[PDB]
Amino acid sequence: PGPFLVIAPKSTLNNWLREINRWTPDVNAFILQGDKEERAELIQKKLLGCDFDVVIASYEIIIREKSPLKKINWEYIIIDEAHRIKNEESMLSQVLREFTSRNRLLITGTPLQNNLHELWALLNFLLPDIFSDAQDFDDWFSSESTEEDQDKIVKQLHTVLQPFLLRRIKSDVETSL
DNA sequence: AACCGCCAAGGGGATTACTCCCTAGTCTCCAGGCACGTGTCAGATATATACATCCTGAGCGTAATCATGGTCATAGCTGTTTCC
Image (tube, rainbow, N blue to C red):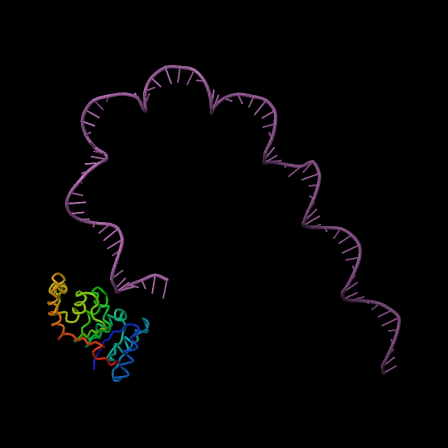
């Protein structure tokens, strides 16, 4: 049981704290909310005191709290609704390539929205030392064969990501019928 | 209610190529506009009167002030009454 970092949109920080209490009450988590002073007593007392397991913050708070969070090495950076990361220049991306966690569990509700460029934008922060490349990934696959429309080289895209990534749909396993 | 991040997409600023026709240089030409004489008029000049206007009281009005009277308040005196 160690240091954990999870991120939720402002509207959703209640739910994750609510569900963690309902299901596994043994984990120390905070909703890191409040004012500049009201975030401080969280910083020095509990966050600096290493008196927690997970920390629930918002999109901007981590940017507001980048410096007091670097000094704590993490286990995962749990990223719900990972849509702000679609842009590499979205400032949240440059604040997350700076933290040092052993694993980096990105989470989403919907997959990539528009482009292959976007796909490895999610993918490049997953295993950065492996790719370390931006346009190399792109012209390697050449955008679903945008010129020849072979639509068979897409199988190579699928074959790497199938044992590297997991999709399930509601229609298959209803759970709601 | 500013700040700051964020988000996508037209929008027009940039760049490249080209074409061309208008302005430049020359050159031929001439009358317009600038120097060059000249008279006449409208500003300058020189008084005289009409008039405005300021100045300082001629006087007049107005208020401020002192005078003056009346009136009321209070004090003093005495007459009345009651009590020993």
